Image (cartoon, grey):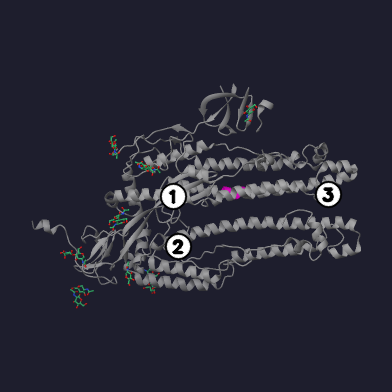
Amino acid sequence: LPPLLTDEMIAQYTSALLAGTITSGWTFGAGPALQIPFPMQMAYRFNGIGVTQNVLYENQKLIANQFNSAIGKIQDSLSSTPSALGKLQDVVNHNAQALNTLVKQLSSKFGAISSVLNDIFSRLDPPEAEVQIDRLITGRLQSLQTYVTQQLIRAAEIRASANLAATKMSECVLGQSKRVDFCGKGYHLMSFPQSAPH
Amino acid sequence: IAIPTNFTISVTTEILPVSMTKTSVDCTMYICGDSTECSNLLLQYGSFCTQLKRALTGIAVEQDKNTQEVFAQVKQIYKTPPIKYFGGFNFSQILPDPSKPSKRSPIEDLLFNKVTAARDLICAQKFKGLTVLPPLLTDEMIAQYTSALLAGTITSGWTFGAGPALQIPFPMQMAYRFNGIGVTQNVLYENQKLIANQFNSAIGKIQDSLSSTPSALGKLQDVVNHNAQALNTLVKQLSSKFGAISSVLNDIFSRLDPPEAEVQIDRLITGRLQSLQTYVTQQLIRAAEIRASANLAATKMSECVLGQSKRVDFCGKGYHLMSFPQSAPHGVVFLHVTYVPAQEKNFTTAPAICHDGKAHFPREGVFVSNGTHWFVTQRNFYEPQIITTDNTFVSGNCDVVIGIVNNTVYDPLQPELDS
Amino acid sequence: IAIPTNFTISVTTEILPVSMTKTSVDCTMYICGDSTECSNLLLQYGSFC
Amino acid sequence: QGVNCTEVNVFQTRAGCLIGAEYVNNSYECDIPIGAGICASYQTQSIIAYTMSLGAENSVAYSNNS
Ligand SMILES: *[C@@H]1O[C@H](CO)[C@@H](O[C@@H]2O[C@H](CO)[C@@H](O)[C@H](O)[C@H]2NC(C)=O)[C@H](O)[C@H]1NC(C)=O
Ligand SMILES: *[C@@H]1O[C@H](CO)[C@@H](O[C@@H]2O[C@H](CO)[C@@H](O)[C@H](O)[C@H]2NC(C)=O)[C@H](O)[C@H]1NC(C)=O
Ligand SMILES: *[C@@H]1O[C@H](CO)[C@@H](O[C@@H]2O[C@H](CO)[C@@H](O)[C@H](O)[C@H]2NC(C)=O)[C@H](O)[C@H]1NC(C)=O
Ligand SMILES: *[C@@H]1O[C@H](CO)[C@@H](O[C@@H]2O[C@H](CO)[C@@H](O)[C@H](O)[C@H]2NC(C)=O)[C@H](O)[C@H]1NC(C)=O
Ligand SMILES: *[C@@H]1O[C@H](CO)[C@@H](O[C@@H]2O[C@H](CO)[C@@H](O)[C@H](O)[C@H]2NC(C)=O)[C@H](O)[C@H]1NC(C)=O
Ligand SMILES: *[C@@H]1O[C@H](CO)[C@@H](O[C@@H]2O[C@H](CO)[C@@H](O)[C@H](O)[C@H]2NC(C)=O)[C@H](O)[C@H]1NC(C)=O
Ligand SMILES: *[C@@H]1O[C@H](CO)[C@@H](O)[C@H](O)[C@H]1NC(C)=O
Ligand SMILES: *[C@@H]1O[C@H](CO)[C@@H](O)[C@H](O)[C@H]1NC(C)=O
């Protein structure tokens, strides 16, 4: 089945979040949006982490250059190591593998003499066809139930991950966090979201 | 820049499921009821009914653990004073109602009523070996815990959750919370009446909103419906052949010989055991999900009710002020009271002030200008003030910062020196 | 005591899964196939669907 | 469990019927959980059944300017 939200709408949502956090600070997440110059917002965040305002105002150019250099380097860092996006690939591979096992399960004899119904029906009498069909039905019901059970477990795991992602989006993007190592490694300044397949 | 000039007090509701329904199953009487033939043949299948009972007992004790962990978080039972004057705030709509014999509150009753010869379905289910155990804590005990929590947070603030309970007037507690969110306390001390009126109006609006709409408690009803659906499916599973000649077994023994009856009985035993195993597995998964929800509810109770939280969008929408808990069938309801700005205005700012060849930065607020003059004001509220040396600090000359303006800085000492 | 004198701005990446593919299955198509007699026998068996 | 023991000391509780335990009118912290707000304990060389106690009792002196 297809998802309800197309990728265009998700990209629109991310762009709206980026514009809101760039041009308004953390105000748009707690009521009416109020504009503020970006350097002043950075001064507010520096004051939040425990550094006086003048430090930013006397070193604006160096901080801007460092930020630009980091934004430049991250793109190259994402373009070389293929193990960075392992998790989504693992999810896709696991789902495809489960489906492949389920579809391949059909050819099994399940103790009977053949896996094709027409041959048993046109070659054997109905009284034994009863037990052969019973065997095949039991096997296929067991396979379907197994598939459903693992699907439920995996869905629960994915729901937990989605809840954690929602909490991170609500706390590190719409505001500034004091929790340690929750939104990075160091003293948190800000965060930006992007969308990826699933 | 934009600066707000007014505020609003808002109340929001959140519903969280906590516990489930405890069930127990009787193996043999479910599988074959009162047939001695099954009573004999089942035994050679070993013992599938030790681990099933073990798992069901584990779920049953886990439910009580969840409820006790979520609700039992106060060492003592507090009581409100007989007089109900709290500086203008009207908490009469959430405090326990003494007239009613159930000792509940005017909302908890709405929650309980909202969630809901011939034979009842419960009796029919019980007549198949499925019994329902009662919870350890009665509803009166849960209401007592909720009332104790409400009295403690109203009377003492957040002090009772970290040691000995310390009393404090409610107005000063609200001033402390306002100072916590980043607004000075003179705002409260000047707008006490308006804030109390807004609080009462919000409480009444929550009253009406819960009273009118009857579809705001979907989660608890969904849990109940899922449990009922599982039990109904298990009951209906008994009237199928499972590959045998007939479902009812007395006919199986009467019509045919013992040899073929053995095969039919084996088929029925295997089918019914498989159905029970699947039911137990689904119950385990649902119990895990309910436990996760109960852990979240316990964390929210610890962090929003017993204190003030700076986590964004955790205890409501806006700047958190406080919270109130209420009970509900197999769940809890949180009322979050928060603070939002309104009536913003445009202003022009500058990073610093270059006066006497020195750069000046604000100490706590921010610099603004109403077109002609310049003031310093707090960030979350409009309160202009004359720029002095008391609320400003100096560092470096004024040829490094970008966007500085000149103005002047008034020193409140020289006028006294000249007179 | 030790006190810092310079700083560095750093950018770190985090990846989180959100959703999973949605699937649906058909009882008779998977189990029986294209034979109607199998469907007639199977409909007597249960309502696992 | 869940059996009216008039068609089975005896005590008829919400969970069923209890035999061998003497009902008292005091209140203690729960030792062995029975159900529906009823617990049991071994106390006094005897076995007793009672209702749970939800902790101690306290009141805080609240006033306008204290
Ligand atoms: C902030 O908002 C409140 C609520 O709207 C304003 O209080 C109102 O004041 C008018 C007088 O102009 C009264 O007629 C209303 O009854 C008041 N509302 C309430 C709920 O009592 C308040 O004036 C606003 N503050 C400012 C500075 O404009
Ligand atoms: C606090 O709120 C309650 C409920 O909103 C008020 O109770 C009302 O009292 C008046 C009497 O003047 C009755 O006519 C209303 O019917 C009551 N409300 C309801 C919902 O029944 C109460 O007056 C308020 N103030 C105090 C001090 O308790
Ligand atoms: C900006 O604010 C200042 C002070 O808050 C205003 O200055 C006063 O404006 C009033 C007008 O009601 C005059 O009567 C006073 O004489 C002014 N004081 C001084 C020292 O000049 C100023 O008018 C405001 N600018 C606006 C509203 O455009
Ligand atoms: C603030 O005032 C100072 C002094 O009144 C201005 O500094 C003068 O700048 C001009 C050219 O920009 C020079 O020719 C003068 O010699 C400076 N005077 C002094 C005493 O340094 C300054 O320009 C003013 N600020 C702005 C933004 O114009
Ligand atoms: C603090 O660190 C910054 C960058 O990490 C240093 O800036 C470098 O300074 C050298 C020497 O002047 C230049 O060659 C580099 O180009 C600068 N880097 C950048 C990105 O511009 C700075 O010198 C360090 N020390 C102080 C006191 O700021
Ligand atoms: C705290 O202040 C309240 C508000 O005045 C007092 O309540 C008043 O008590 C008197 C005497 O019983 C009544 O006549 C008034 O009607 C009450 N006020 C209201 C608004 O109803 C209360 O007595 C004070 N308590 C202390 C300890 O000083
Ligand atoms: C502030 O100025 C902009 C400039 O056009 C205007 O659009 C905006 O409405 C102003 N702010 C308010 C609160 O009116
Ligand atoms: C138990 O049986 C007695 C006698 O019939 C009856 O009076 C009483 O109400 C019954 N109690 C319950 C809980 O069924």
Relative to B304, residue A191 above or below: below
> Which chain does the residue under circle 3 lie in?
B
Relative to D42, residue B5 above or below: below
Q: Quadrant of ligand 5?
A: bottom left
Q: Nearer the viewer, mark 2 or mark 3?
A: 3
Tell me the quarter of the picture where residue B164 sits.
top left
> Which chain does the residue under circle 1 lie in?
B
Query: Label 2, label 1: how many angstroms apart (C-alpha)?
Result: 35 Å
Image: magenta residue range:
B287-291
Inspect the magenta stretch and tell me whether residue B290 lies in it. Answer: yes
| Element class at badge 1 | helix
- Check the image and name the residue furthest to the left: B419
Give the amino acid at mark 1.
Asp
Give the amino acid at mark 3.
Ala
Q: Nearer the viewer, mark 3 or mark 1?
A: 1
Q: Is residue D65 left or right of residue B102?
A: left
| Element class at badge 2 | helix
Q: Which residue is mark 3?
A: B244
Q: Which mark is residue B208?
A: 1
Relative to B288, residue B418 above or below: below
Q: Which mark is residue A173?
A: 2
Inspect the magenta stretch and tell me whether residue D58 lies in it. Answer: no
Give residue A124's position: percent from left, percent from top. 91, 61
Q: Which residue: 58% across, 62% down? A: C19
- Residue contact between numbered discs 2 and 1, judged by CB atoms under 8 Å: no
Give residue B222's position: percent from left, percent from top. 59, 51
Q: Is residue A52 left or right of residue D39?
A: left
Q: Which mark is residue B86?
A: none
Give residue B319's position: percent from left, percent from top. 39, 55
Q: Is residue B194 left or right of residue B297?
A: left
